[PDB]
Amino acid sequence: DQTAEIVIHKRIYRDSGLNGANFEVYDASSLLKPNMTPEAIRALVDRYQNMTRKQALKFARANLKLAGQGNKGIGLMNTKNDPTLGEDGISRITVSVDQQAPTKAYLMIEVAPDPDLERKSSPMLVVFPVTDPISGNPLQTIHLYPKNVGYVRDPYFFKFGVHPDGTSKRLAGAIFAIYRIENGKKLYLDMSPVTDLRNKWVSTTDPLHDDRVNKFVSDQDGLVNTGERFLPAGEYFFEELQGVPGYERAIKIEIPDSWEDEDGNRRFVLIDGQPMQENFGGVVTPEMISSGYPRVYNYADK
Ligand code: NA
Ligand code: NA
Ligand code: NA
Image (cartoon, rainbow, N blue to C red; front, side, top):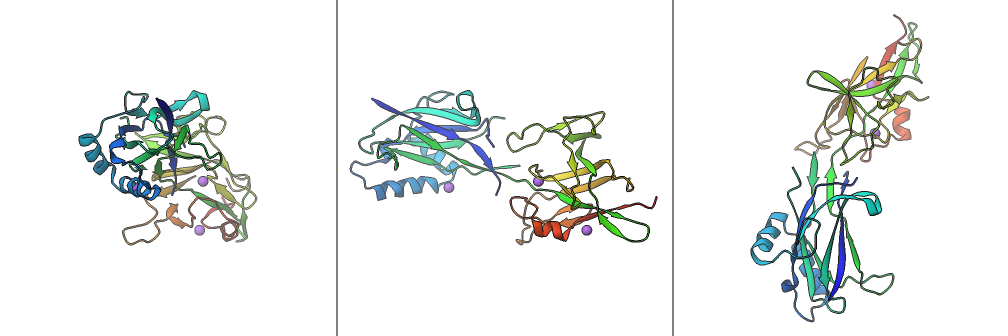
């Protein structure tokens, strides 16, 4: 009789649309009883939410049937680009609902993605109706935001110049690029938009003048900052493409694969071996700029 749309927006968060995620959707109406309380409903939703995906799949595969018109078939959803909203990570399913009494429900569980990412989605039990606070009315479209976590870090350093008389200063106008090594070849961090919380890398004959290659310029505080750009675990290099006049190099970036070690202690990004202070979210603060560490010293005296 009546139908509703469930829309998954699968995105990547750091503790962003992710294509190729897969979900199975089961008719869960049999988990419901007539004249259930809202409290009983919330208790049943929490029970399924607190199961692992594997646990919920053992229960659903054995006992329930796929249901709903998904893009991969009955009960089958794959995340893709949505031209209608120009956003990635989108999958829509049409399901049979009862907007007047809680008698229809769907259990949605992520399965293996299409052939550095924590897939943290939970089993999601959608019990209709879902009442719109704003309007009173039952919702006709449910938007779900299953959680995926990408691990990224935020390298920066300060460029200082040292005079032969031992005076020193922050250097403005040094131009850097970032490269990594793959099969004995340099790939440079490009200007392409991030997809799946992952960067694009280009081979170039001339990184300084190649518009594809992202450049990072030292500012009036000496700061060379990735800024909005981030990197995942591994080893990278800031390469000086144009030195500051009078102070005319690869600076190694070592990114650990986790914020904390087995004992809870911070694992630092190392800049040419120096531990780099960092906050969650990666913003270089005014206090960090005052500190001006880690510092790379460029010598005037040839
Ligand atoms: Na959970
Ligand atoms: Na950054
Ligand atoms: Na330093």
